[PDB]
Image (tube, rainbow over all chains, first blue to last red):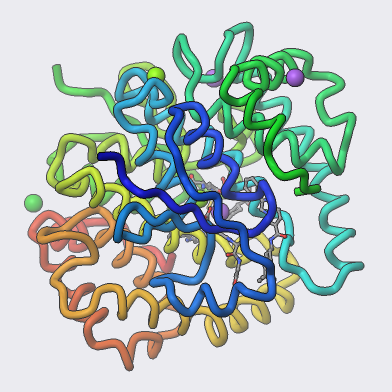
Length: 200
Length: 200
Ligand SMILES: CC(C)(O)[C@H]1CC[C@H](NC(=O)c2ccc3nc(-c4ccccc4)cn3c2)CC1
Ligand SMILES: CC(C)(O)[C@H]1CC[C@H](NC(=O)c2ccc3nc(-c4ccccc4)cn3c2)CC1
Ligand SMILES: N[C@@H](CCC(=O)N[C@@H](CS)C(=O)NCC(=O)O)C(=O)O
Ligand SMILES: N[C@@H](CCC(=O)N[C@@H](CS)C(=O)NCC(=O)O)C(=O)O
Ligand SMILES: [Cl-]
Ligand SMILES: [Mg+2]
Ligand SMILES: [Mg+2]
Ligand code: NA
Ligand code: NA
Ligand code: NA
């Protein structure tokens, strides 16, 4: 039968949400294991590397959110439809992840953390939004003729950015339309209704 | 027909080197276009997301070094020998890239830059080296029974780290052995002999 899938991450959307969307879209059953921050050192001690999310697939522990997402979407409708499309999917996702990963999520000094979030959102985020809008143009989805997991990743990253900067897309209605289209995909809409509500 | 490839990056190994290794290994002819930092301000607006490397292929523009590397290795013996091993390849590459991407390559204040390079090399690089070494164990390659582009990426990243900290691997003979194996692969050895000599 199907594998036993167990996703481990914090009780946040964060870096695990892309995998959660993929499982929902593919209608694949999984255990959505959410740990408290206090229990990270114990979990970490059991892993080959030093980060979450990780995905157990039967007896195998996978790591790296995008490596996992790519694996789960291979040979599904969420992959790019062609080899080149798969390159473009990968590139857009890495561009989004690169930007999200610039935020000092783990900075313990709160004043330093807030200053850097504000700088990134005020002076850098608009340039990424403009690059993404130009890249999308008048097309329905970011890559090819149908939805890919890059579209999911756009909606996920932008949801978190909008928490901190609600007017991020005021000048980019086409990027708003794309978010709404992802959110209206039935399996995604259903997951959004039912998922734990967390800030991040 | 023979493909028309043009790689654009700075005159450094940097983030383009993985692509250069793959082109060498696959016997692919390409234009290795190297810009100087003084060319950057005028090239930036031509780039899809404001970053290099980019790769032009038969009139199309690709970006994101690892997206490009993955695209070039699909259907080659560098990709990973099973779908699950391709996931492992991808995860190792992202773990390496995540670490290299922590370094403040573009920091202006040189004292701030040096402090952070030293901190990362002292208190974070040892954990990565230990985790990689334990993952490799007694195996010949990082993933599977033959070389993959993750092994290439290990050698590339560690070569640069060793510029700053020559002693970094003195306690990890198995990781040194793996570097030397990559460096002796005929295509790689010959590329190393002929490539432009740059610090980074
Ligand atoms: C246990 C510990 C070491 O103290 C951890 C330190 C990191 C922290 N982590 C965050 O607080 C966080 C929250 C939200 C979030 N979202 C992204 C994101 C989203 C989409 C794409 C890429 C990245 C990264 N994030 C990190 C969680 C605790
Ligand atoms: C002109 C400008 C906008 O100011 C640029 C800002 C970035 C800087 N960039 C570096 O100076 C640099 C040097 C070496 C290097 N090596 C990696 C590396 C290597 C292996 C794997 C992943 C990353 C990244 N690097 C960046 C070059 C100038
Ligand atoms: N590129 C990795 C990044 C993973 C990552 O940074 N995870 C953070 C949680 S948001 C983590 O595990 N931090 C714990 C630590 O650094 O000890 C991925 O997407 O999986
Ligand atoms: N993850 C991207 C990162 C690309 C990147 O940041 N490249 C640097 C050159 S080392 C760049 O374009 N910097 C331009 C800038 O800092 O404004 C990739 O691997 O292609
Ligand atoms: Cl040769
Ligand atoms: Mg598809
Ligand atoms: Mg990355
Ligand atoms: Na990154
Ligand atoms: Na474009
Ligand atoms: Na909506």
